[PDB]
Amino acid sequence: SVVIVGKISFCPKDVLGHGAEGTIVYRGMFDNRDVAVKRILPECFSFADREVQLLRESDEHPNVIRYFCTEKDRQFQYIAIELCAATLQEYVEQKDFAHLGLEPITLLQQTTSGLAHLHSLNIVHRDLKPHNILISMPNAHGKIKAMISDFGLCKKLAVGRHSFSRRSGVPGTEGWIAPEMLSEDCKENPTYTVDIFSAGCVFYYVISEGSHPFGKSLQRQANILLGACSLDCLHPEKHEDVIARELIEKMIAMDPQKRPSAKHVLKHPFFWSLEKQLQFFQDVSDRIEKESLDGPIVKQLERGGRAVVKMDWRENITVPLQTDLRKFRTYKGGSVRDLLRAMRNKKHHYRELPAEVRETLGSLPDDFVCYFTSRFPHLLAHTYRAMELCSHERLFQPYYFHE
Amino acid sequence: SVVIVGKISFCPKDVLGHGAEGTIVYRGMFDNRDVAVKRILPECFSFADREVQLLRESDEHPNVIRYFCTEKDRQFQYIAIELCAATLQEYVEQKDFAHLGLEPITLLQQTTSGLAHLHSLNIVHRDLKPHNILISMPNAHGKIKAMISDFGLCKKLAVGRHSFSRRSGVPGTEGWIAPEMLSEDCKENPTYTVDIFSAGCVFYYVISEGSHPFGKSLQRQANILLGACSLDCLHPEKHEDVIARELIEKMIAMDPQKRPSAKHVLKHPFFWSLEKQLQFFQDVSDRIEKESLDGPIVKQLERGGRAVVKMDWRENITVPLQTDLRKFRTYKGGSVRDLLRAMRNKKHHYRELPAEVRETLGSLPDDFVCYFTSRFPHLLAHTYRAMELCSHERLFQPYYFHE
Ligand SMILES: Cc1c(CCC(=O)O)c2cc(Br)ccc2n1C(=O)c1ccccc1
Ligand SMILES: Cc1c(CCC(=O)O)c2cc(Br)ccc2n1C(=O)c1ccccc1
């Protein structure tokens, strides 16, 4: 028995899953393309028409599911969309991340792009969770991508409006709904920020390989409203983790105003290569070199540096570098600027530096930059936030978001 | 009136254009989606079957036209694809260009990208012309993109093969058909290069604002076969023109094996920012600083450097720079490396230079590099080709294509 509703065809025996509101998703064909078919019931025909329009308006982007067509029966309405190979959930739940390279982060970056695309179209998803974040089929050359799905609970903000009342009840799924949506009072109407919070938890769900910032399933929602976030899978003294901690912590704040935008999250160091990181260090040092001590830039860079530098950075580096630096007298052990200024000098002159000092630093640029991030795991986080005072400047545009 | 073929609807009174073999294109809609439908007559039903299938294997790429569906009638066959705003022909022939800034080169880079994608899928267009390059309908934010269409005459190379016999006549338009396609004296059958020759003409067509590298319309195909190419639109002593010459002259090469691949074209200086050119001069200089004069790299950089440096480059730079460099007699005016190094030095210590030598150089980075490209209009093209000996080096990966 093969169901043929117009250009869509599927066999009822091939069920890919069950959805809510009696929606059943089969595997089928459309225009000889492999698609997933969704049967919707008359009780939901209206909810399905809005999802298709919001899909038609965004599937162009590579990180949004591709909507194809819709055919109607005397009994059902069928939605044909691009056939994937797995959800992010089964991915986090069943891949050997050790063999998986930097894929997990690029999946997080792609999902973030999709969100910024949707937010550029005044579309809020409201139901972002690892289940409806899909993994594309492997392409002709063997690559996969992440795409956003389940547009049933999406909302297009009204022209000229930048929030949305809580009239659609409490859209979303327990454990991933931001507090404003579930809180009994209405200090302010929700907005795009409810998506970041969901996204923040998802970032952690991937980098923890299964954990949630707000506890286990049954107590999540109650912790979310109570503010009981715990990012335990992230060391406090690891460079990578300290950077992730900064981002995810900002993404799951209780005040949705203090939550970053998706365009900001795309620029975050959490996504930077080592080559880029070292580059950010070089440019900060050059911008501050002739900045006075009374200047705001330098005063923000040095507020709280003693902990960043670990009291005295000269007492925390390798002996071959300590001796090399002792040759002159131009770097203070308490200055985070001078630590960055030292990194600039020892990079420029790297080739004309004694082999013993070259061997402690490592090859450029990856081993060089790691030398200083492992020793001072708060250096990038501290200086990134400090240098925000120069996000308008052309030189720094590659690191912040500032239209 | 309006003809409704299944989910495709159009009005015969809305004709967008006419093709070959009686194929008419109307403006229409598919699934509430503004599309352009194609009416295909019976003698041509098989050409569409191929095009549709090929389109379904590559339409995903942002710069390859998006194909939606295809229905059939009692006597006709219809094909609905993305509706565009113009073709590159109309864009070139009817756009100020003075207020278009750099949009035209972004277009050339986009059609290249889509063509590299098609080649990665073992597909040769074989009929690339400013007519098949359509411009996107403006976005939800006012941006456009170029795309490739007219896949009817495309060729999916046999499995493992990297060439194709001329068994299907000579597909393509008089004026854009590569010479290997028409001649019988050729021993080598055509490959993907045949698409690069055509693109190399379009490249020139766009920068010349309509002109062709092989003359006027009727004598064009005649001139192509004879190798008589003329790019008089490009000055022989202007930095920008020298670069575009180097690339175009290699894409329209008479010998197919001398033509850059699509991925090669994508890295050519023709597409670099001003800052990227500085970064190239800096990396080239830094890389050759500790290289033996007897070394192959140095011997290739100076092979012909006399015309490049215009004899003593110290005598072709502004006087203020001439005085500030007179103290260093290390710089040999007949060395291109010495010129590149003098640039590297002027860039690093730019802030500590006397104001006279700073305002004669210009604001970093754009005006600084222009100081040398305008004065030495062969410096880049000379260095880029000679330094190919280092294309394999990670340092230079941003600048060349290896694998
Ligand atoms: C696109 C798609 C949907 C629709 C998503 C939406 O629009 O909400 C889907 C639903 C279920 Br249940 C089950 C599978 C579904 N699937 C897939 O292709 C797919 C997902 C995981 C593994 C293999 C294939
Ligand atoms: C999508 C599209 C097609 C189909 C391309 C194909 O056959 O692959 C088309 C054909 C002609 Br003729 C003419 C126009 C065509 N057009 C356009 O949107 C368009 C292009 C330029 C100016 C105005 C509209």
Image (cartoon, coloured by chain):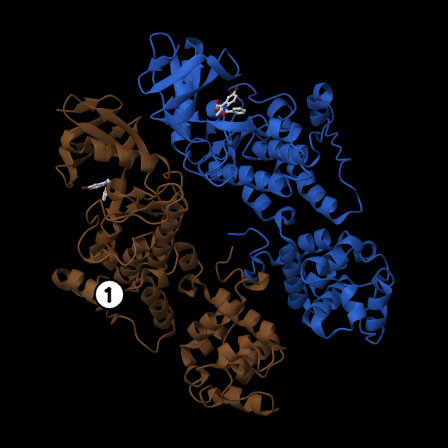
Chain colours: A brown, B blue
- Can residue A159 be seen? yes
Q: Position of residue B173 (x, y in %)?
A: 60, 21
* Left or right: B102 as drawn, with respect to A200: right
Mark 1 secondary-structure assignment: loop
Q: How many marks?
A: 1
Residue at the spot 14% in from the left edge and 24% down from the top edge: A75
The three-letter amino acid code for the residue at tag 1 is Pro
- Can residue A137 be seen? no
Quarter of the displayed picture in which ligand 1 can be seen? top left
Q: Quadrant of residue B82?
A: top left
Relative to A54, residue A247 above or below? below
Q: Position of residue A87 (x, y in %)?
A: 24, 48
Kindly identify which chain the residue marked by label 1 belongs to. A
Residue at the spot 51% in from the left edge and 85% down from the top edge: A335
* Left or right: B191 as drawn, with respect to A197: right
Q: Position of residue A209 (x, y in %)?
A: 24, 62
Relative to A69, residue A124 above or below? below
Residue at the spot 79% in from the left edge and 57% down from the top edge: B305
Residue at the spot 66% in from the left edge and 40% down from the top edge: B99
Q: Residues within 10 Å of mark 1 (few under 14, many from 20)?
A: many
User: Circle 1 is placed at which residue position?
Assistant: A213
Nearer the observer, B381 or B40: B40
Relative to B58, residue B274 above or below? below
